[PDB]
Amino acid sequence: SSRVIVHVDLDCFYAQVEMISNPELKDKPLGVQQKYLVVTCNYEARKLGVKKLMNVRDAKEKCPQLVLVNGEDLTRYREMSYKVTELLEEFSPVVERLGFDENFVDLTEMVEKRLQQLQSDELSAVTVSGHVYNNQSINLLDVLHIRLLVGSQIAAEMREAMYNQLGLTGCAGVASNKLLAKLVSGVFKPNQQTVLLPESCQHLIHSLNHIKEIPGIGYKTAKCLEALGINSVRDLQTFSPKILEKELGISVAQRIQKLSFGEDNSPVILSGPPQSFSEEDSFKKCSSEVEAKNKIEELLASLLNRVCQDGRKPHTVRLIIRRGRESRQCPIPSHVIQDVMTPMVDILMKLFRNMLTLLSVCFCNLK
Amino acid sequence: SSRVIVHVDLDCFYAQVEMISNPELKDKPLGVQQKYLVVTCNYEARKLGVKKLMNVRDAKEKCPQLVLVNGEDLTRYREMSYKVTELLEEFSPVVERLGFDENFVDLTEMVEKRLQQLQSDELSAVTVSGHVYNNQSINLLDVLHIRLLVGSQIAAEMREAMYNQLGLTGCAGVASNKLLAKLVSGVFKPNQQTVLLPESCQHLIHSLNHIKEIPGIGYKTAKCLEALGINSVRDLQTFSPKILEKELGISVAQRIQKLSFGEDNSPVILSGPPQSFSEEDSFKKCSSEVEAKNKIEELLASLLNRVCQDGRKPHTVRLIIRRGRESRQCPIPSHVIQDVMTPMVDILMKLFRNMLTLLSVCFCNLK
DNA sequence: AGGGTCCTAGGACCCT
DNA sequence: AGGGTCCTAGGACCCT
């Protein structure tokens, strides 16, 4: 029942893609901006103090030299994202996408195969690729250390192939479940990998400074927990399972408390093709008229290109607006499944009439 | 793009099953009761005035001779229901279940096969099995009349097999879509079949006396339509598509108005195994204590037997209560997927604590 | 921002 | 009653 999981986490993905386009952008600090927010920056910029999602002003304050670059159109990032997932699917088919720049792979079946092909004398010659978390000592007769080290060898092969075949650097973390692989992938953060041996699991989770930092524990469950006096990982570990049950639920409770201990039995899901296709347009209260139809015609403009090129067809469209958000959705008529936009704009226009700073159209329920 | 669909509608299903158990119950009027309500009755009882869902009192008023029989445990009905669906799946695999006693089958691929095997001279020798709606005249050079007549021959073979192999009588309606097949299956109502030729589609839908009677038009959309002055099928046919769009939605609108015309492009779905397993317990305010745990232990008692024997395992449980209803659900822990009830009662007990005349537990999200 | 994921609790519909 | 179906609109989570 042992598992070997790798978390692959590309460095400043958007920046990497832009720096590939215009090679001149390298060397100097680089921000990728979405409206008034630098969402991503290359290492240089990050050394100068440009932080994740920093105002284009505060960016130009710690870093007047910034060479900013617009990244509101995610097409090129989305395409490279899937080129990376597909490269990893070639290693082992079971790859889970988390956002655009992170992937989980279950290396278990693959690690086991590489061992039965390996020979007796090799077992002692097994080496780690990259760092070992907390410099922990390897025990070459621990079957679990050997598998995690083979896992680190596969992880380094993936990272080498991502660079060689797509020009992308990134980090990797090798552990026995998704939680720990993701928590250890970032220990050595620029284009490196780390492997976690079980004896250091507690050191790793306790290296966190607030249950905020546990993936699966967002703002809501965080502030909720902070209202029970739970703040450190150890607090959540020792807190009453009972009060937690009745406070957050039976679902949230035991999952969160197990994450507290480094436990995470959740399987690596095959992400396969997307379950949805959305696009967003925000503006300085630019919508209060039939302009919404010029936008929406534009949002949907590029989508129909996307949702078509995919192959499958959506059987539901949705329209989203900001003024918390609201949505009104409807099934896509059969006739409209196969010129469109005359019929589709109309669909979403009446969805729009039923219901302005944001505006989005999402194609979902694909078949 | 022509379709041949059969709607199979067993007569007083519950009664049929009971009359099979204790053959003595035949001959005399028979009611199947659920609390203070005769939900089903054999033809005899129905001749005496016992109507669908009639008080056990009003039942014993038009029909003091009633020989009532309890039918709150649906196990035996549910089992025969699936024996009937499986018999029809043998004819053609694509069978859609609607409730326990109704099934749709798409006979198109099957009718077409029977024709290419049939010979030239036979085409004129094709006959209808059962009634033709509105006594309409057959045109043996109308390819659509011939296919619907082959459809009627398959329908009669199914009904003969349901009787011969399961002892069940029932009705059948043969049409070109689901709506019309279901509307015509009941024209000759006791253990007979009817076929609808297209030239009589309008006669059939206009034979209805209120859009209430169109399947897919329930109480809500009905009263809504009745507020627009729409009452007859012709009203809905001629009513403004536009006002209907803005009143009921773009989804409801065109689907409802097409049903008005006898149009229904919806495909026959393969129902396959159930998507859920529920059981219900209602009582005269009998629950206001740890009794709910004695019930719930009992509701869930039989379910775990059911949801297990199926094979797949649910990955969500739900608890439902009446005091409109309310539900609180949660994922079923991995450990509990495989003794249970010690863990499961507890799960639903805390779901119960979070939230008494009704009480139910439902196992859903099966895999 | 711009973009995803899956769940949940209520609601409509079908049948008896 | 006792039992099903699928949808929807909001909400939580992940990433930038």
Image (spheres, coloured by chain):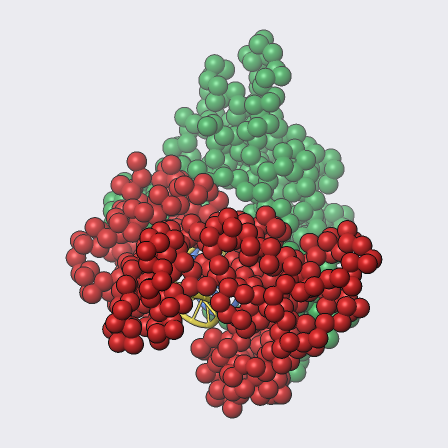
Chain colours: A red, B green, C blue, D yellow
Residues A255 and B47: in front is: A255
Pick out the residue farthest to the right. A120
Tell me which corner region of the image, top left, top right, bottom left or bottom right, holds residue A42.
bottom left
**Residue that appears at 69% across and 60% down:** A150
Q: Is residue B248 above or below residue A309?
A: below
**Residue that appears at 61% across and 66% down:** A130
For this view, does A90 lie left or right of residue A222? right
- Quadrant where the C terminus of chain B sits is bottom right
Residue C9: x percent and y percent?
49, 70
For this view, does B276 lie left or right of residue A299? right
**Residue that appears at 33% across and 58% down:** A25
For this view, does A193 lie left or right of residue B17? left
Asked if one can make out residue A324 in the rendered structure from this viewpoint, the answer is: yes
Asked if one can make out residue B352 in the rendered structure from this viewpoint, the answer is: no
Pick out the residue farthest to the front. A27
Residue B31: x percent and y percent?
64, 55
